[PDB]
Length: 300
Length: 237
Ligand SMILES: N#C/C(=C\c1ccsc1)C(N)=O
Image 1 (tube, chains in turn brown, red):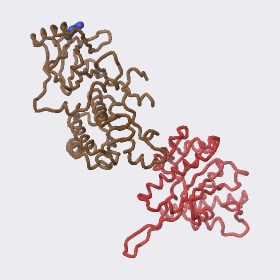
Image 2 (cartoon, rainbow over the protein chains, first blue to last red):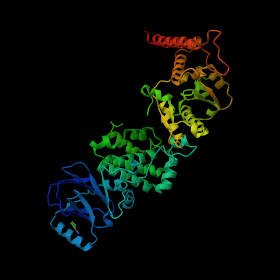
Image 3 (tube, rainbow over the protein chains, first blue to last red):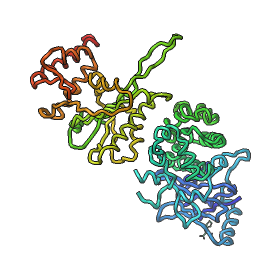
Image 4 (cartoon, rainbow over the protein chains, first blue to last red):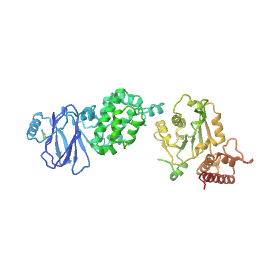
């Protein structure tokens, strides 16, 4: 069990750690988060009390280094930092655990929610979507735009998700126009799975990461990307049976975890009604269709 | 974006554009089967692709053989239309290719857009106008060539005859749409108006009668009357 310690909490902020969150008061004696489960990526995120504008945060994996947070009063945010000195950082942390100044990652033993939301998400792929190669962890916020968004403006601060476009030469074989537009299996299986992602785990990882950025940061381009990757599967007549079964589980847990009061902005009516009721896979997402119908029957 | 009454003069500027109407591509007669069920029998159709500035009509005849063994024909018809429009553009010299294609039905937008991906600089546009191009098969010579075709065929017409020698494009298009609106609202009477007499004939190389300027004013007046009436006869007013 690993620890994301803090230098101090100089400004009042709501701190999120994965799907949990807690309020810290200005200058409250707070020195971090302990008992973080090893084996999963994590995200630690922030919303200042003064400026609910800009949710921001950091994706990280404690196996990859020792990470600590210090508030920067010039740039005005809580920054993640890595410490090479394994011995100095530990002595500072034990000291703090002794004084009980850390909150405990509050995982219920029965609960597999985080695993289920991050099953295929790996840090190495996060770091290729979020390009900042000098750090082991990745910053994301509400305002960052995607590569595809910048084609329709700072390339350094973009989310380099895989571009999906249903009316594009990549998506449509010359002479198969109607066939490929109405049945996207070619584009799913050959172009994206075999060609770009290599396997369905990497596809699902990007899909899960897009959802999490949409949910935790209100990142609109991430939300677009999540829906596009869902729609590409649902609009394919030919999908491996194991991918459909896993997609149903993935979406079920995303829909289960979504805040009930964010469903209006985070869910695209057209995509979901097409996917659950009109598409090739309308009958293949039993768990997802059942939770959607009992929790968000208005959208549909 | 979409084409409407506010930007109507844009049709007659010097950017090449084509209207594409697909309403006559997939045409059927509905009949009873011996078992008392209902069946369709397709008849020959056509794509109506029209330059509104020059009057040039590219009439692609759709022979019923193209439907053989195919499913969901109304959906295929839109994609067949887009394939043939795309083939037509590619056959034109670059300096003849359109800069915009306006589809009369919004369901043509995605099929044409996908077929024209090679042409990113050709704008595909809908329209809010209710253009009467479905009535093109009420033009006798157009109907005749469609129904006689035994194979896929493209036939080229000028739907304005020689009108541009005496009137502007805007005026010729207004005349065309008035003629077609009349034919669409009451074909018999529209056709009675146009050729019930002897001395105002159709040249072998024309579609419409050889009317003098004054005779066109009477004709146009009679078509307006028909259209207003049918609109009463329909709503009782
Ligand atoms: N180690 C360390 C450092 C700061 C800490 C470490 C955990 S909380 C605050 C540092 N090198 O500045």
